[PDB]
Length: 318
Image (cartoon, rainbow, N blue to C red; front, side, top):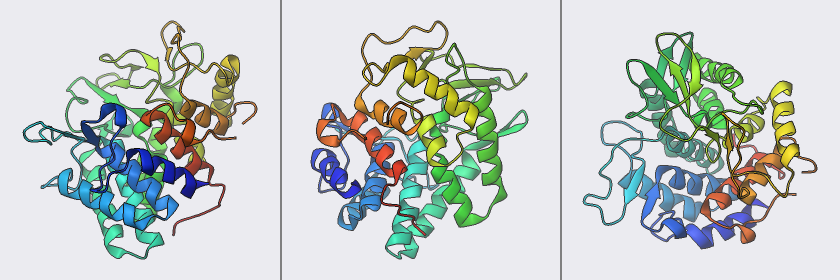
């Protein structure tokens, strides 16, 4: 149950000033982490926590000249938020959490906050690429005159759906629909999996695995099947492909990464958060792991996302 799992997450990673901090990377907070804290506390109904997590993120990470968020606060760096680059998944997670909080607690200011973020994602983080409108992963380091790099796991599909519900802007429909087209096509290797990082050539529209990171399905890409399932956008074709992958390795041996150019897998197995995702997307036979057994912060956050997607309590924020 979400409130009980949030209580475990909160005990481990929440601080009274509103910061979410991974105990194993104790000198930083991220926009994605504040977004998770806000999303989980909104889903669990913990308004006292939500309020301080949002105030901390707004005060320390939100930009002056737009509504997006600097990706990291680095303790002891002078100044602590020296890199102003954003991470679009953090922006979209924070916006979704504000939308949920504003609906459940009747707070029009939280709805306005969400709409300000969504407006700037649409304005600053979309680009026309070939026949598509794409969602950029951040302002710096992903777009050149020759190629665009996309992170398909930054298509936080329930957040894009919320943005359309709030605005009625048909461009959100185009971003989502082109995203599904890109995900269908940008799959690689013997398992036909999406990469952590995709490249589209701006002069030819050819798709490839992006240079600059190992050519893997791993810690980013494993969100993709989760967001597609959660948003009811996972096609039969794709569900069958993910199911074949999970069941080849089995619940006891899911890989932490798979190389999409040669099929090599990590020697070690994935954390329980991957099992949570697989259980929602075709693994035989699907109950969710609990956070008291989480080996690390990454796994705990991914497992919580799976609890929210499963929505056993059948809550809908409106």
